[PDB]
Amino acid sequence: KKKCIAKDYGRCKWGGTPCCRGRGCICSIMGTNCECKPRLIMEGLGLA
């Protein structure tokens, strides 16, 4: 909500807020109640 999500598994949308720290945005069985899939050190970081 309001400038990125900031949470692993955050109930995102394609056409909304992106995702901050923990990303993806694959949806449920509707396209609403989605999730920002779990990745911190597999996003833009890698190690630290």
Image (cartoon, grey):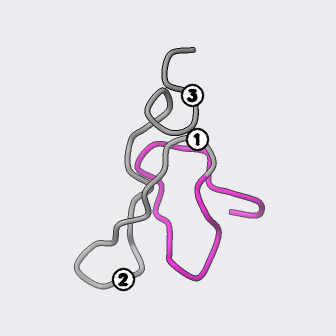
Above or below, comparing residue 30 to residue 18 in the picture: below
Query: Which residue does the image show at 77% across and 60% down from the upper left?
Result: 3
Q: Earlier in the sequence, mark 2 or mark 1?
A: 1
Disc 2 residue type? Gly
User: Which quadrant of the structure image shows residue 29?
Assistant: bottom left
- Can you tell which of label 2 and label 1 is closer to the viewer? 1
Is 41 drawn above or below residue 20 in the view shown?
above
Number of the front mark, 3 or 1: 3
**Mark-to-mark CA distance, 3 and 1:** 10 Å
Q: Give the number of the disc on residue 45.
A: 3
Task: Specify which label sits upstream in the sequence, 3 or 1.
Answer: 1
Instruction: Give yes or no for residue 42 being in the magenta stretch.
Output: no
Q: Does residue 3 appear left or right of residue 29 in this picture?
A: right
Residue at horizontal 63 percent and vertical 48 percent from the top: 20
Give the structural element (helix, strand or loop) at label 1.
Answer: loop
Kind of residue sitting beneath label 3:
Leu
Question: Closest to the observer: 29 or 47?
Answer: 47
Write down the residue under mark 1: 21
Dot 2 corresponds to which residue?
Answer: 31
**At numbered mark 2, what does the secondary structure look like: helix, strand or loop?**
loop
The residue sitting at 62% across, 54% down in the picture is 5
From mark 2 to mark 1, how far is it between C-alphas?
A: 21 Å
Location of residue 6 by image quarter? top right
Query: Which residue extends farthest left?
Result: 29
Query: Badge 2: few (under 14), some or many (20 or more) residues near its Cα, within 10 Å?
Result: few
Most common secondary structure along the magenta stretch: loop
Magenta residues (range) = 1-19
